[PDB]
Amino acid sequence: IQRTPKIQVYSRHPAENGKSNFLNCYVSGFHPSDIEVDLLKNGERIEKVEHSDLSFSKDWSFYLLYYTEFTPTEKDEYACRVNHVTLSQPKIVKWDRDM
Amino acid sequence: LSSPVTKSF
Amino acid sequence: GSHSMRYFYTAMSRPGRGEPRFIAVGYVDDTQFVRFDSDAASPRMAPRAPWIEQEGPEYWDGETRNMKASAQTYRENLRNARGYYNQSEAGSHIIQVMYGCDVGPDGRLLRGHDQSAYDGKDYIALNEDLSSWTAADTAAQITQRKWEAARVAEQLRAYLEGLCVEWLRRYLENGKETLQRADPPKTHVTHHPISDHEATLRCWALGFYPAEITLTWQRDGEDQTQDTELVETRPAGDRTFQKWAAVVVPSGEEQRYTCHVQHEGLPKPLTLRWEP
Image 1 (spheres, each protein chain N blue to C red):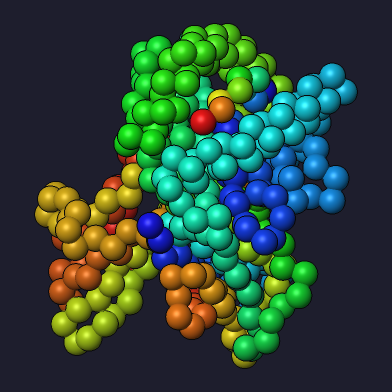
Image 2 (cartoon, each protein chain N blue to C red):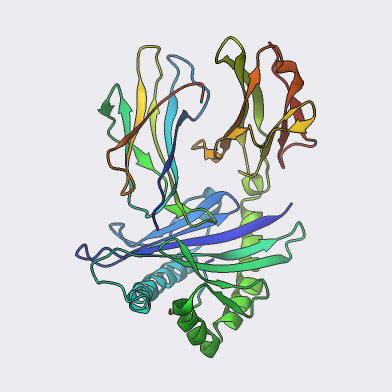
């Protein structure tokens, strides 16, 4: 009846400190469609975050890509905060250049 | 081009 | 070589929050080209690919009218479906539809599809024959009987064999430079020690189009299907996709592992190893 979202946090191109890029949060495999997704820069919500139009896979589960332009640095820490009916408290997935 | 076919359940 | 056109419809009820939201997205393979959202300030069928922008006013007006009519029909379907399942008027429910055509390199119909779901479970599907239906339960049988009486399968087959095939062939010609171009993955293997005796080998594939790809790890020429962690193929945000496959190997045994990559964009399957 209800499916929990799979979450992936990664960059559009490989991460290079000081070079412009896009931070992505891909939420998939979830059901129903209602989902709350936030992109975090050092624990604070990034404003202006855009997302893909709602669509779904062959197994009927939904997927969305949430993205914003960013400039990675060695200091700066990024994360994705996701909430959905299947989750008691919001889930934080930290951005890792190596995943 | 989308389906012009009415699918009333 | 082979191509597909698909439309994905989501109709979600929200009692006490107005009328059900209806969203339609059109794709050619893994490229979205159109969207319609009833929740937009001014709902219209809107371009989402440069090659579709060239379509005239008669196209956009014909498609917008069709979407509004589809939105109305699916709003009624949600009322009927709630009734068919003896459901409360308080709950939020979802109807989903995915339909379209597959063509070969010659652009001839390979197969047609028309599947529907109710709350994420199969509800009714048009069979490969494009003449009969597969109802998942007794509620979907009522829909079946209404469709068998109105001969909906005939009207679908006529769309799926005619218009769907004709229009996809046109889109493929219009979007020639992108739709008919396969971008091979950019590949590499990373190595991360876990312990004194273990390390992770990660096989990356980036910048590939379309999304379809095979990434496998072999140990001594034997597939490591069970011990391979495979992430879901993910969009980069620029039309392309990304995927990785990881295997945990004993230290010193890294050279016994090979990553195998199959993609439409590659002339021959790639074989890569960790290059220390």
